[PDB]
Amino acid sequence: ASAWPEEKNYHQPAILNSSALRQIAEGTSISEMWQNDLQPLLIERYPGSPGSYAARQHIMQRIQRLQADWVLEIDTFLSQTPYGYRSFSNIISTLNPTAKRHLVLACHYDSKYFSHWNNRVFVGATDSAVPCAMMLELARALDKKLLSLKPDLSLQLIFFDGEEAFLHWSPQDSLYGSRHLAAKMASTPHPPGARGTSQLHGMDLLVLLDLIGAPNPTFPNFFPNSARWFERLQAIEHELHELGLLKDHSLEGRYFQNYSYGGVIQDDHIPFLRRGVPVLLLIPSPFPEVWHTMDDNEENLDESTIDNLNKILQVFVLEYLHL
Ligand SMILES: [Zn+2]
Image 1 (cartoon, protein in one colour):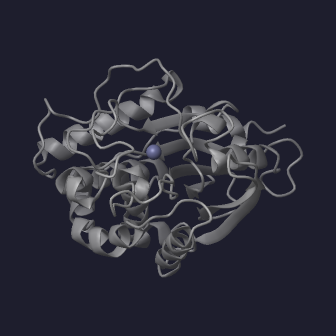
Image 2: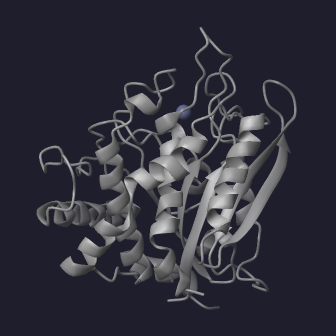
């Protein structure tokens, strides 16, 4: 019985030097992301809505235009909800589908349902349009390097549907897409033909982004089994900073601070965490001031903070995949 599922326990990053770091910082464009990946997603997109359909087409189209060999799958299912049975569709974008191991980045593309109020519409800018856009900008920025993948380890992106409760949170009303996908992955043999390993055993680490985009985010070190990766985020943030590659940034106001947070946060990582998947959680604590409010809009986003996190995330991914 091969011990490949244990390889993630010992995987070490291939650290980028200064020159490569400047290259990555210069390779990403916050303005390009803003216009081409984020704005099209700032629309009402709760499950089953026209906006949900449009967001999916946007996410799919932006990935399909890239050179790397992304395999796109739409995972569609029915679930009971407070409003009766409804259909949901997770979007999975995978490089090297038969690769045994994958580093996984994830977020949710649905927006929380609210009836229009005073002609205001909830578009969930930090929740989670920006994370969706950061993942698309990461695919774009690193396209040339990812193309070379065409450790038996690759990259996967998941855009969950139905993360949000239709009413207020309850065990049965929330995480529709991730509860569904986690059980499906746990019961799908991997790699193809495998006798006793599942897609879940194949997930090296789930990097989950949500509620990102507000000013001064502080991300705590949530879990001991991914602490050494949280430390790499800190090391990367620190070096990008020292090299003068971040904007409007200081170490005292650093994003990754090593304080723990013991409580549970309800988001898409939960169904995976509870089945044994190591999670690196990029959800700040406290949550943005505009959380679940009509003010979670474009106007309240912090552009240089998103740009800074894009650089950190991209360096982290390259170092993880040895690219
Ligand atoms: Zn939310």
